[PDB]
Structures are given as structure tokens and as C-alpha cells.
Amino acid sequence: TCPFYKKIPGTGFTVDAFQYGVVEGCTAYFLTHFHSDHYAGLSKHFTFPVYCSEITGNLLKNKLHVQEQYIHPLPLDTECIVNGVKVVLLDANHCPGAVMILFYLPNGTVILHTGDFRADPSMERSLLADQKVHMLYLDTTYCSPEYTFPSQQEVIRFAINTAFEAVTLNPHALVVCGTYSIGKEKVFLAIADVLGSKVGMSQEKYKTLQCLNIPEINSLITTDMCSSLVHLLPMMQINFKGLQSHLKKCGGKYNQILAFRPTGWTHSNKFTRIADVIPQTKGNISIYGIPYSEHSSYLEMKRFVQWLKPQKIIPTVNVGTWKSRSTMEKYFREWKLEAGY
Ligand code: NI
């Protein structure tokens, strides 16, 4: 059944709750972003109101074929009324179109649901600065102190320098980047840019990217693989077998592959710096795992919560085991005592 942490008290609202059939008493279904564990269950047959960002609305229409009359996009950073309740959508710093949702309850309670987010100090100067938030439904993906990672900026610098050096040394090298969802577009766009190439991809992926309102996108991507030296492939194919196979397909236009796998966290983060990363190599193929995250580090999450000073925290990630629940609740109390709220 629909879990309590997907329900907004005092409303008929649910968040990211599309796989339970009809939720008894739900008058509006919000969708934070277009990732499959969140939209799971939506289709052309859905006949309730869906509230979301413009970009998420483009993806629902074009990729899932949800009918237009049930899609209600809202602009960001704007006070809106939905079934008699004031809401605001804020940028979540996750994937394109991803939002956090502020609900202003008739009784005076204010609730923030983060969806999936990467906490940033820039959020401290949004509409969140303007009033008190009583309850926080929090993206706790990496809520443990072992989870450190570099800035997105540091990671992109590393990838750009690496790719540029490789291709300038060998003009017959191919660069490949893995993907399995929206998000992390900076990785492959920044590399294609330093190399003066467009990124080549399947028709399905090109369609997905054309929904995202990225400026000048027609200048940066293409379905013509042969004219491109940065290819995108399914993440599943980013391994030595899948890459040798792929290399055959290019007809001796290339003799070397340099491939990037943008992972979340991986335990080499507890030892190694970004400057010190190395690839796995077999033959003329090298694969780099780069820790490009679109979720908060432990320290980023801690800072955001200690700034906001909520009265109650409701985790939305890692809630399935008692040991994870109990560990998270321990960090929350530490944070509150350290900061004095
Ligand atoms: Ni997500």
C-alpha cells in the first residue's frame, strides 16, 4: 500500500505515488522528476491530475504519452493555488526538470518535500529563506559520513582535460559515455564541446534530450553517429565486451576507445582524490568511473538541514531496514544538538 512518507497530511495530495493504483482520497498526484522509480506506473491511461514542472510535463507527453488534459505544469519560484492549497516548486539541483515542493497548509503548517536533490548553499537564498518550515521530507540517499564526493565542477574539469589530451595524442580515438536516464548531461556535453564534435546517440535518446529546454541544443547533439566522435550508449554496454563490439561497428574509423561511466558513489572515494583516478584498461579500450553525483553528499545534506532547522524530518530513501532508519535518526539528533534547534 502507499507508504505514509508519500502522503502530505491535511491535503488530498501524494508525491511520487503512481504505482499503487488509485490512492483512496487523493485529489492531485505530484511528480518531482522524470526518473523511473518515481514515475513508475504512469501511462496514456492515467486520468487524474498530475502536477509537475514544464520539463517533466514535456517528458510525460512525449515519452510516456500521458494525455495533455491531465498534465498540469507549473512555473518555478511562483506561488500557485492547487485545489485550494498554496504551493511553490523550487529547483532541486538533481536532473533536468527536477523540483522540491513547498506546501502551505490551511492550518499554518509549512512542509518542504525535497524530491531527489543535491543540496547547495544557493538554496539558502530562494523563497525558502522567507518563512519557517515545520516538516521536511528528505532525500537521504547518502546520509552517512563515508559519503564524500567532489564538486560537479571538479569532476567536469577532470573529464574535459582527460578527453582532450587523449584525442589530441590520438586523433583516431573515440570517446564513449554511458547513460540510463536523464541527468548528468554536462558530462557528455562538456566533452563534446572541448573536442568540437556533437554527441551522437540513438533516436530514442535524442528525443528525450529534445524535451529538456537546453539552450542551443540543436547545435550540440545529433543522430548521425558517423559524423560524431563522442557517442552515448546504454550504461549496460559500458564494459570491454560491449565496447569491442561497438568498435567493430565503426568500420575502422577508430582504433581506441576512451569511455566514461558516471557512477554515484563508489568506495575508492574513501581513499582516492579526483586528480588521482585511473582507468580499467584492456587492449586499446580504457574505462573511467567518475563520481559525478546528483544527490547531496553527507556534509551538503547536514549543512542544508542545520540551516533550515525543521521541527520534524521524514526520510524518503533507505527507509526499508530498521538499521538504516535507526542510523539516520541518530544523525538527525546529532545535527539538532550541535546546532541548537
Ligand atoms: Ni532521481
Image: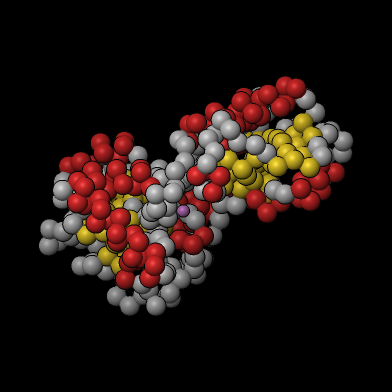
Decide which of 129, 87 is in the foreground and name it.
129
Measured as percent of width and height from the top left, residue 96 is found at: 46, 44
Vertical comparison of 254 with 60: above or below: above
Decide which of 328, 53 is in the foreground and name it.
328
Locate residue 39 relative to residue 208 in the image: left or right: left
Residue at image location 56% in from the left, 44% down from the top: 268
Measured as percent of width and height from the top left, residue 309 is found at: 20, 49
Decide which of 312, 275 is in the foreground and name it.
275
How many labels sit on residues?
0
**Colour mode?**
secondary structure
Decide which of 309, 185 is in the foreground and name it.
309
Where's the N terminus, which quadrant?
Answer: bottom left
Locate residue 190 relative to residue 69 in the image: left or right: right
Measured as percent of width and height from the top left, residue 273 is found at: 53, 35
Locate residue 234 relative to residue 249 in the image: left or right: left
Measured as percent of width and height from the top left, residue 297 is found at: 41, 45
Furthest-top residue in this view: 168
- Viewer can see residue 180: yes
Furthest-front residue in this view: 271
Locate residue 134 relative to residue 249 in the image: left or right: left
Furthest-right residue in this view: 252
Q: Write down the quadrant of residue 136 in the picture.
A: bottom left
Residue at image location 35% in from the left, 65% down from the top: 325
Residue at image location 36% in from the left, 43% down from the top: 299
- Viewer can see residue 15: no
